[PDB]
Image (cartoon, rainbow, N blue to C red; front, top):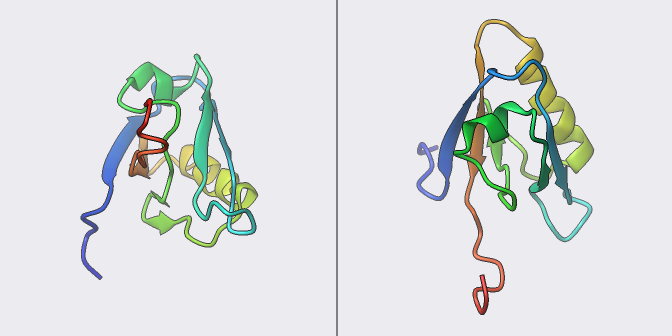
Length: 103
């Protein structure tokens, strides 16, 4: 399996004391991958700025969130924060072009 052309790997360092990110969707729901609906201020992601509100996590630290439920994902991401081996979390987003008419 190739590296992955569709998508942009985003590295978020655990700068903040606690990661604060919100998502929605899930396999069950029309949306297969989780989409960022809210990005807490005191969260590594935000502090980074690289990421924005409205992204879609397709892969985290190598683990793909395909066919996974938002809940199952929340755990995957969190687990990446607990560990110490790495001082960051990989966030693969595509920034789908939802309703280009306006945005």
